[PDB]
Image (tube, coloured by chain):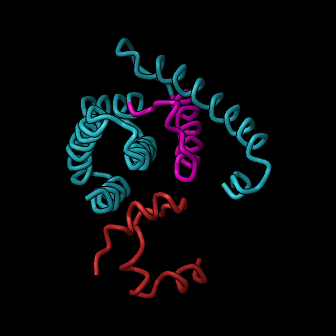
Amino acid sequence: HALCNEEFTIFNRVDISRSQLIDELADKFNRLLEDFLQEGEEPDEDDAYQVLSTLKRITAFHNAHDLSKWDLFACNYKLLKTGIENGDMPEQIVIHALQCTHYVILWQLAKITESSSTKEDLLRLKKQMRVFCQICQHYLTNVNTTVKEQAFTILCDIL
Amino acid sequence: KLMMWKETGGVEKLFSLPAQPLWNNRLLKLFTRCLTP
């Protein structure tokens, strides 16, 4: 983010590099998630480690970078839904998914300011917001104290 | 970590910053513009 300042004449190069990095991360995340959930059989542990590792990087970058063109809300929200439905997901996976989805919602708002977006985008943002709060509430009354702590922080800031 | 918490632990900063740390000034404005008088 410090090297991606527009006023400096390096945005083209740093943006090319940014685009490659985020692209590889996104393709790997989607490919891994397809086999991860899969609805068909039981998942292993090393692939869970890889999924957590990739998500920890996507989340870390989505806090200062507008990773919106690579729409991930579907992926994160699906992952969280399978988590509620089964009740066996890893805690850190839940935490970082719950973080990345807050980030995508916040950036979606960041782009609703120019007024270039139609009324459909505002209603889409409302639809994503109400969906998010509902999932966060359940995760505010979980067994894992780390999960409940992350829920509280995110819910308070969103409100 | 204690240096940071002495930077931001003051209640004036505790009541003017997000709980989940947001680094980009865009998102910081998205939050802090909701801080009225």
- The colour one sees for chain A in the rendered image is cyan
Q: Give left or right: position of A49 versus A17.
A: left
Give the vertical position of A131 relative to B7 (above or below).
above
Residue at coordinates 42% horizontally, 40% vertically from top-left? A90
Q: Give left or right: position of A111 versus A29.
A: left
Please state, as top left, top right, bottom left or bottom right, where the C terminus of chain A lies in the image: bottom left
Span colored in magenta: A45-73
Q: Is residue A129 visible?
A: yes
Q: Is residue A95 visible?
A: no
Q: Give left or right: position of B23 versus A1.
A: left
Instruction: Between residue A95 and residue A108, name the one nearer to us.
Output: A108
Give the vertical position of A115 relative to A75 (above or below).
below
* Picture quadrant where residue A7 is located: bottom right
The reply to whether the magenta stretch includes residue A57 is yes
Instruction: Between residue A116 and residue A19, name the one nearer to us.
Output: A116
Q: Percent x, y for residue A92?
A: 45, 46
Instruction: Between residue A154 and residue A19, name the one nearer to us.
Output: A19
Q: Percent x, y for residue A108?
A: 40, 43
Residue at coordinates 63% horizontally, 35% vertically from top-left? A22
* Picture quadrant where residue A3 is located: bottom right
Residue at coordinates 40% horizontally, 39% vertically from top-left? A116
Residue at coordinates 28% horizontally, 40% vertically from top-left? A122
- The colour one sees for chain B in the rendered image is red
**Mark count:** 0
* Picture quadrant where residue A128 is located: top left
The reply to whether the magenta stretch includes residue A46 is yes
Please state, as top left, top right, bottom left or bottom right, where the N terminus of chain A lies in the image: bottom right
Instruction: Between residue A28 and residue A19, name the one nearer to us.
Output: A19
Q: Percent x, y for residue B21?
A: 48, 63
Q: Percent x, y for residue A155?
A: 28, 56
